[PDB]
Image (cartoon, coloured by chain):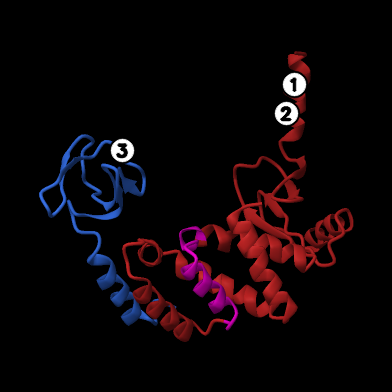
Chain colours: A red, B blue
Amino acid sequence: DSTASRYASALADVADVTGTLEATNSDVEKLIRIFSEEPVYYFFANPVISIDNKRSVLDEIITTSGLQPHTANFINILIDSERINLVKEILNEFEDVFNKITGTEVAVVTSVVKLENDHLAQIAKGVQKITGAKNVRIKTVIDPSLVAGFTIRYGNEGSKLVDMSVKKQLEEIAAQLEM
Amino acid sequence: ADEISKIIRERIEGYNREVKVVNTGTVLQVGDGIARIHGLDEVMAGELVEFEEGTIGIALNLESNNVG
């Protein structure tokens, strides 16, 4: 694994044993924008700064943003054992272990134009039956870099892929190249 | 929620500004003639540094976070 992986899995475990999965997801989504905006991240980093000055502001952020009492405990421990310089990685990693625990898959639909959502629900149902997702969190982006249609990227990160926008001209140029 | 906790944000800025002074670092570790310094963002490689006791050093190792 990794430090981010092992810490995010511990957070998801302590947030699943006492069910706050929606609450801890909202809390980590608030914490991702808190620990973005790089001055405050530098401040909780920058080990020259006193730990007490870190912890004062950390408790005040707990108060102002209404965080959960176990996610606040998690960031207190990230301050205690100096893994706070990886907190961006830990928060970016928490979403994957959260999707593993909630059995959700998340798969991008890079298309050209928007959809009427019926074929999108069809694609979501297909990608949830082929992967065993009890509730796939299908997503999409509007990208003009594509040519014609759509493609799905599911699995771990984007590990699997079926594509019908540009694959046909790719195989046509490969076939006429005959090399 | 920082736009709401703007007072907390300004206190964070005030805490930060004490540490990131220009041409000023802070000793992280020191022993056996080697020092690790936090800061000194605008230091040249091979520049001379001073250590508040008159001990002089040379910045040979400019890593991303510290300076050897």
Chain for numbered disc 2? A
Q: Specify few, some or many for label 1: CA neighbours under 10 Å numbering under 14, 14-19, or 20 or more.
A: few
Q: Are marks 1 and 3 on the same chain?
A: no
**Mark 2 lies on residue:** A170
Quick check: marks 2 and 1 in contact, CB under 8 Å? yes
Which circle, 1 or 3, is nearer the viewer? 3
Q: Is residue A26 visible?
A: yes
CA gap between label 3 and label 2 equals 48 Å
Name the secondary structure under disc 1.
Answer: helix
* Left or right of residue B38: residue A144: right
Residue A65 sits inside the magenta stretch:
no
Question: Residue B39: x percent and y percent?
Answer: 27, 53
Q: Which mark is residue B61?
A: 3
Res. A58 image quadrant: bottom left
Which circle, 3 or 2, is nearer the viewer? 3
Q: Specify few, some or many for label 3: CA neighbours under 10 Å numbering under 14, 14-19, or 20 or more.
A: few
Task: Please tell me whether residue A16 is drawn above or below residue A99 in the rendered image.
Answer: below
Task: Please tell me whether residue A81 is drawn above or below residue A161 in the rendered image.
Answer: below
* Left or right of residue A20: residue B46: left
Magenta portion: prevailing SS class: helix
Residue A77 sits inside the magenta stretch:
yes
- At 84% from the left and 59% from the top, the residue drawn is A128
Magenta-tinted stretch:
A68-86
Mark 2 is on which residue type? Leu
Mark 1 is on which residue type? Ala
- At 85% from the left and 55% from the top, the residue drawn is A131
